[PDB]
Image (cartoon, rainbow, N blue to C red; front, side):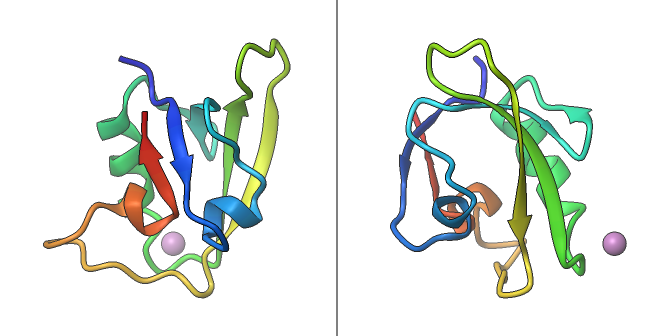
Length: 92
Ligand code: NI
């Protein structure tokens, strides 16, 4: 169930934030995200914002990292597109 990254598009907003395949997204701006729909819901709420901070769990790591996404070049159409894709992420 948990939101675990499978691939990361080169040069994407996630690639620049150093998010790596097999990383799990634990929170978006301190709001826990137990699944991908919860990630999607939080990201939609960042429309218009310059940045958001994600807390991630690298693969098989116990360490948790806060990573800042730069959203100043971000656009997606919320009726037609998956926000998770628009960040460079392919779910596992
Ligand atoms: Ni805002």
